[PDB]
Image 1: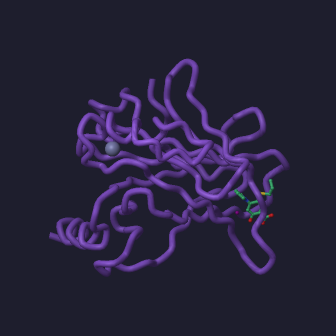
Image 2 (image 1 turned 90 degrees about the vertical axis):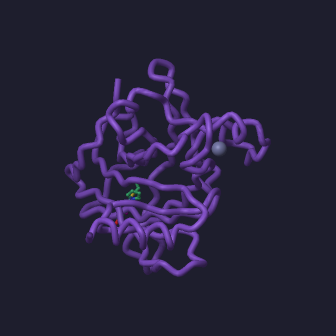
Length: 196
Ligand SMILES: CCCSc1cc(C(=O)O)c(O)c(I)c1-n1cccc1
Ligand SMILES: [Zn+2]
C-alpha cells in the first residue's frame, strides 16, 4: 500500500511552516515555497514549524514518514542505503536503517510498521514556548538523495501527520526533500528551471 499525501488541515487547522534561510552557498537547509521542496545537507538540522488554529487534545502526536514521489516507486520503503545503515552513527534511539530522525527530543519514538515495513518517527505535541506562536521540530535526513542502493537519485516526499493518541488522522501536510551537498545552489537551479 501507499500512505496518503493529501493536505488536510482538519479540525485544528494544522499546517507546516518553514524559515526563510536564503540560497547562499553556505546554507545547510533551505525551503522553496514555489517548489514545496526542502533542500538540506546530510545529517544537518532541518527546522519544521507546526501551526494550528486551535489547541489539540493532550496526547496528540506528530509523525514524519518518507515516501518516494514517483508512482512507480511509491510502494518501495524509503530506507538508508547499504553504506549508511552500517556506519554506526546511531544517536542511541533511531534505528540505523531510518532515514528521518528527530534531533534533541528524548520522547521521540521510531516505528517499523509490522504490516507495511515503513519507517516513521513520532513525537508528542508540546505547546509553543512562552512568547512563541508555533512549535518547531528539528529533523535530520541521514542519506543523500543520490546514495546508491538507497534513494538512488529518486525524489522523496516527507509526510507530516497530526494524530490522536490511537494514531487516528487529525491533519496532514507534506513537502518534497532533496538531500544534497549544496542546497542553496540546487534550490536556485530548480527554481530557475521552474521559471523557464
Ligand atoms: C497537545 C499539547 C498542545 S499541542 C499545541 C498547542 C498549541 C497552542 O497554541 O495551544 C499550538 O500552537 C501548537 I503549534 C501545538 N502543537 C504542537 C505540535 C503540533 C501542534
Ligand atoms: Zn546513504
